[PDB]
Image 1 (cartoon, rainbow over the protein chains, first blue to last red):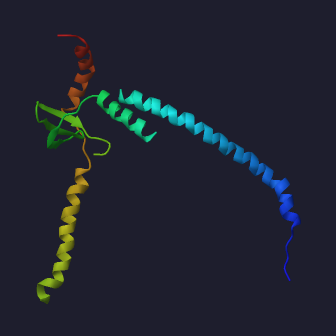
Image 2 (image 1 turned 90 degrees about the horizontal axis):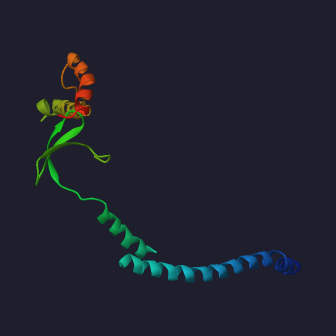
Image 3 (image 1 turned 180 degrees about the vertical axis):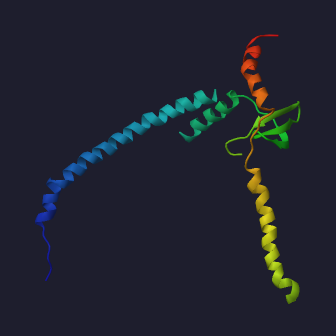
Length: 50
Length: 51
Length: 53
């Protein structure tokens, strides 16, 4: 019975998964970005109110 | 972002000039209407783009 | 109630047409104040305005 390969998963890890891993590094970068951007609208929020 | 934007948009409305308030007495034949501006005199004036 | 009710439906079409005419007409608004010999007046009139009195 059955039909599966284990060869395929391992291959997918070296090849395809590494390119997804570059993309997850970018979402890290996004994380950092929206700290500075949050602080900035906070400065502007005060300036508007004045 | 929503909050800062609104506080600035209400300020923009203040800076741009006043409004008044009339009542349409009749319709005239150039696609203008005879308004009586309630606290002042009459002015004959063009329709809007929504009216 | 046949003698008037049959034919009444026909009149209601006529009332509807009387509604349709007034709006159809009111859609078209144009001027001119005065006549053709006073169309000459404006060509002059432009000038007499730019002058102050």
